[PDB]
Amino acid sequence: PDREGWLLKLGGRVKTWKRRWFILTDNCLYYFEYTTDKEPRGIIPLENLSIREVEDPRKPNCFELYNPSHKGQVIKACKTEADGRVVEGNHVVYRISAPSPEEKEEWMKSIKASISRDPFYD
Ligand SMILES: O=P(O)(O)O[C@@H]1[C@@H](OP(=O)(O)O)[C@H](OP(=O)(O)O)[C@H](O)[C@H](OP(=O)(O)O)[C@H]1OP(=O)(O)O
């Protein structure tokens, strides 16, 4: 309460990938820069979002997080700036890459189960 591990994340404004430790708990995805950090770098509520496999030109074992009900809106999420101050995220989509084909399978299964497990999923 359900899965943890390293994954790569593509930046919002522009590109550049970053390695972050992710924690799937309470239908939310928390991420940190280092496993020893005391406070979250960000929080992404999973409710009302979907996940799809994608083919990135360079990074293998990828998938994306997006909002199927509001094309064009920024995904509601929290993140901390360099100075530590909290602000809203600016992602319309989140692209992620896993460490191995098996782990990608594991993460997509866990995320889908988490989302569908919600009483409001329908
Ligand atoms: O542009 P943003 O939408 O603010 O995304 C930002 C990125 O900004 P850019 O893509 O414009 O370079 C950051 O890149 P950098 O470390 O080079 O500043 C980083 O990639 C950060 O990642 P980090 O918060 O894990 O450090 C993202 O924040 P997110 O958490 O929202 O992805």
Image: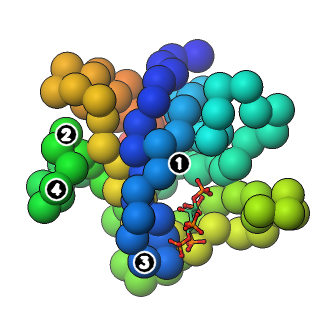
Secondary structure of the residue carrying numbered label 2? loop
Q: Are marks 2 and 4 in contact (CB under 8 Å)?
A: no
Residue identified by numbered label 1: 47
Q: Could you tell which of marks 3 and 4 lies nearer the N-terminus?
A: 3
Q: Which mark is residue 111?
A: none
* Position above or below: 62 against 93: above
Where, by quadrant of the figure, is residue 94 drawn? bottom left
* Residue drawn at (40%, 44%) of the image: 8
Q: Which residue is mark 4?
A: 58
Q: CA distance from mark 3 to mark 4?
A: 16 Å
Total numbered labels: 4
Q: Residue furthest bottom?
A: 72
Q: Amino acid at mark 1?
A: Glu
Q: Amino acid at mark 4?
A: Arg
Q: Residues within 10 Å of mark 1 (few under 14, many from 20)?
A: some
* Residue 69 falls left or right of residue 104: right
Residue 122 visible, this angle? yes
Could you say which quadrant of the image residue 100 lies in?
Answer: top left
Which corner quadrant holds the N terminus? top right
Q: Is residue 67 visible?
A: no
Q: Is mark 2 within 8 Å of ligand 1?
A: no
Q: Earlier in the sequence, mark 2 or mark 1?
A: 1
Residue 9: x and y, percent? 43, 51
